[PDB]
Length: 331
Ligand code: HEM
Ligand SMILES: [Ca+2]
Ligand SMILES: [Ca+2]
Ligand SMILES: [Zn+2]
Ligand SMILES: [Zn+2]
View 1: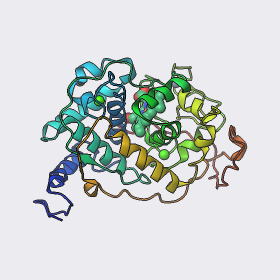
View 2: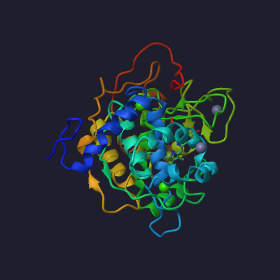
View 3: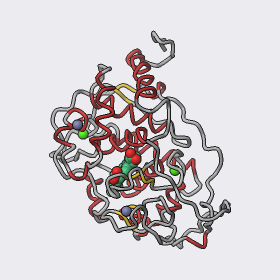
View 4: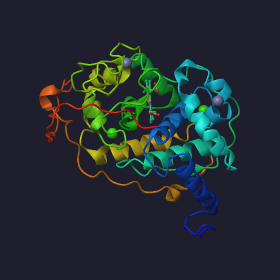
């Protein structure tokens, strides 16, 4: 019900100002629409930003962009290690806009995630007011935290157990650079450029290795594949009685995870916010997956630990060379 300077059509004139910002992001941040490090980092940033929130107060203003506006404070916390890199890349591009910090952070994550084939078209609201103060320390879960502690933290923000697992489909387009300091950008699945369910499957393969210097760095546990990092907390969720059957649910069920991730993200990116305008039609529709998921080369069902023997895991093909090595996400 309107048409904007740059041409495109929308439901509200307020949404018209988002189209130049989306070009600035794709050019100057996402290396021309890639599902690379900066796309992944933008998603991570949105979570770290939004989880500075508690329904009972005292833990920050939520999805307010506090992590951008007050980064000198928040990027000094341990649990935010590596965030400073994202902030440094986002801050100059932010300044070429008149958005609030919250509206920028969460649009960058909506756009970046969509550069990943297989991801759901994410909702995007805007009109967030400026963040007031930095979140306090300790709002961001750490991979050594217990399952109990992590689910408790999420509850405070307003999320149930299942939603925590669906939110972790993010790790399908994700890597670690602060655990293995000599091995930056080590992915958590085989296909960090694709938002598929590979992640869920490769985390239940038997852990036999350690990547990089082959040593036990603190937040990681044994990985099934060379070049792949497995977080201690991801493996905890994958094996824990409370969550192991939820963990297997998405495998090769792309539509299942698309809806669950779309809905949990819709809530996450508005935590602590009220009174926003819907602008989801500015958000590009991400490409689809070129085909269903397959076992990595040299793996089969033989290699899985089923903590959910209540459900037959779905059959799937298995590319055949030798067991591969996954390179780091590019820079
Ligand atoms: C549930 C508890 C979670 C824990 C313990 C956790 C932990 C971690 C850790 C340790 C890293 C690697 C940091 C580094 O060393 O570079 C990471 C990366 C990442 N996290 Fe999670 N995370 C959690 C939940 C989430 C959620 C809810 C989202 C978003 C929906 C998310 C999105 C990401 C992304 C995209 C990355 C990759 C960043 C990049 O490659 O640049 N995480 N996470
Ligand atoms: Ca925040
Ligand atoms: Ca993936
Ligand atoms: Zn900085
Ligand atoms: Zn390591």
